[PDB]
Length: 67
Image (tube, rainbow, N blue to C red):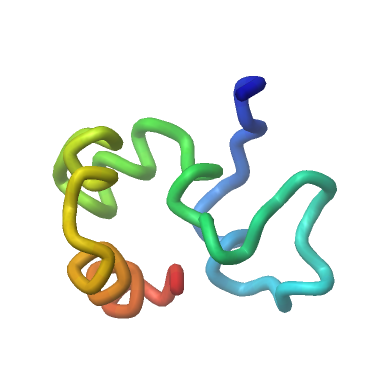
């Protein structure tokens, strides 16, 4: 797929789902974090996160309010 736009952490965390920007999937919030944000938040590579079990991916997201 086409490369996704980047949005700051605070926007992803603080914005109601129907109010998020165009093309922003509020169930895939980690995919819209800048690389610096992602690395800062999840301490691992995108691919490493994406190879994690769903439960683990979701529990990481819930602890960071990104679920």
